[PDB]
Length: 105
Length: 105
Length: 52
Length: 52
Image (cartoon, rainbow over the protein chains, first blue to last red):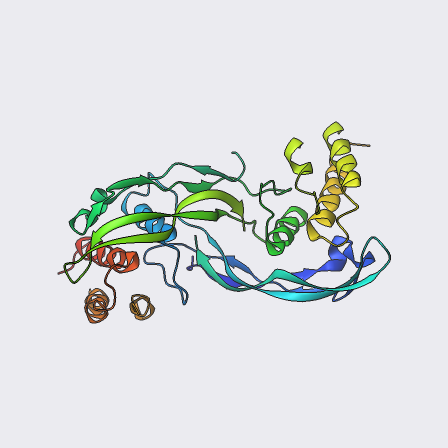
């Protein structure tokens, strides 16, 4: 069991039947977050004060509070060319699509 | 087992030996997040696109991707009156101290 | 604005209510991932077990 | 700026290195929760098991 880190997550729109309205892309790397959330919190970006407090309390008395969880903390958008409900081809920049860093919250 | 929700988390600064530098307050309700992250994602605030995609993939093939996790999505600050390293009494508004809503990410 | 989250509050009769709500709010949701995801989930829950 | 996260990268000798790093970066951290939390964690890890 390793600390909170980023793993792969290959999203394939054909696997969800979304290729009927999505033109491009049809698959992309979205990543995901997984790993232990123990003390201390090691991260390139500073954790929230609440995450620090909850992780410290779980380190003190684990019977009381549950630990923090490994979740995305930075995300980047991707462009999608699709067909909306009005039969129009739309190029839209969807936000929060690719995980760029994980952290304990 | 219930869905992702907010539970209590009474932080007591005396339990962490922080009363030597913290004047007031000495305890406060910080809450925390816990609960199942299943489909669909029910929340007052809209989940991130990545959370939607990962939850849908876990609903499709749970063997592949792990589910999303219940974490804070809105936080509010609290004021703390403490003594810094220079023997000065400082009133500082610490951000991300109280969980106001939980969600799956 | 897209009102896809309004349908998740009241939630095979519940599946039909979810479907009707998604149909009612399908106008403003021209291209929202939550709408298509909720439709896919409704279909997966109707196919699962025994619904019609 | 407070450099408390710089000490978490290299991490009873490791505990002494963590303590020395926190001492070195203790100037800019006038009132940061991460600094006090790291100090409390160093103390808890030194008291645990057998360290001195």
